[PDB]
Image (cartoon, grey):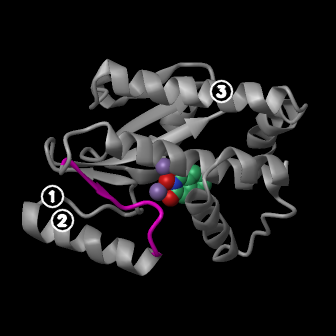
Amino acid sequence: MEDFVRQCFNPMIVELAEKAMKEYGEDPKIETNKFAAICTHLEVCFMYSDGGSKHRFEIIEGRDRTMAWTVVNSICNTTGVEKPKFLPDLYDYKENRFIEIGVTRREVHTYYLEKANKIKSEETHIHIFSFTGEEMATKADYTLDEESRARIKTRLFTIRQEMASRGLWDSFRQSERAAA
Ligand SMILES: O=C1Cc2ccccc2C(=O)N1O
Ligand SMILES: [Mn+2]
Ligand SMILES: [Mn+2]
């Protein structure tokens, strides 16, 4: 699985995933499922940010924590938007809300509720993707056009197929359950 990750995602994503794990005392070489998941989540965030008009989104995820908070503070102090308790993934300058992006190997609505009760915001938009083509967003407002969401869904299903073809998929699906 370690090698699958490094040949599946680009080096920039992999490098960012390693940092993220190390700061949490996780080892990519051992917790290889978490490594895949972080890479996947990062890839979706970047695809999502690319789905809008050029200036639309502030990317928060994949930054150093401290600079992530600084940027969040700047957005809040300048839009008047409520400061979130937890670091979100993006800020949408068009819709004027933060976005939390989730990617789950379980049902989309289960994950959606866990994420919603954790953040406790009537402001932060939530948008979940599955490895099966399902999506769920706050107030059925999916933010992006169909084309952009579809590309992401396709990519996720390719990742699943690539994993399955190597026999890594069961273990990767089970692992999110054994975590929760
Ligand atoms: O920043 C985080 C941290 C995290 C931790 C564990 C599971 C999902 C996430 C997640 O989706 N984001 O965005
Ligand atoms: Mn995040
Ligand atoms: Mn997220």
Which residue bears the numbered disc 3?
A: 158
In the picture shown, does residue 48 fall above or below 9?
Answer: above
Q: Nearer the viewer, mark 2 or mark 3?
A: 3
Please give the name of the residue rendered at 73% of the width and 75% of the height, measured from the top-left corner.
Answer: 25
What number is the disc on residue 75?
Answer: 2
Q: Position of residue 112 (x, y in %)?
A: 49, 34
Image quadrant for the C terminus? top right
- Say few, some or many: other residues with alpha carbon within 10 Å of mark 1 (under 14 / 14 to 19 / 20 or more): some
Disc 2 residue type?
A: Ile
Please give the name of the residue rendered at 80% of the width and 46% of the height, measured from the top-left corner.
Answer: 4
Q: Position of residue 79 (x, y in %)?
A: 9, 60
Q: Position of residue 132 (x, y in %)?
A: 62, 20
- Mainly helix, strand or loop, the magenta region? loop
Give the side of residue 50 with respect to residue 1, left or right: left
The reply to whether the residue tagged 1 has its Cβ within 8 angstroms of ligand 2 is: no
Magenta stretch, residue numbers: 56-64
Cα distance, mark 2 to mark 3? 35 Å
Quadrant position of residue 144: top left
Q: Earlier in the sequence, mark 3 or mark 1?
A: 1
Disc 1 residue type?
A: Val
Quadrant position of residue 105: top right
Q: Circles 1 and 2: CB distance less than 8 Å?
A: yes
Give the side of residue 130 with respect to residue 61, left or right: right
Cα distance, mark 3 to mark 1? 37 Å
Magenta-span inclusion, residue 62: yes
Disc 3 residue type?
A: Thr
Which residue bears the numbered disc 1?
A: 81
Toward the viewer: 162 or 57?
Answer: 162
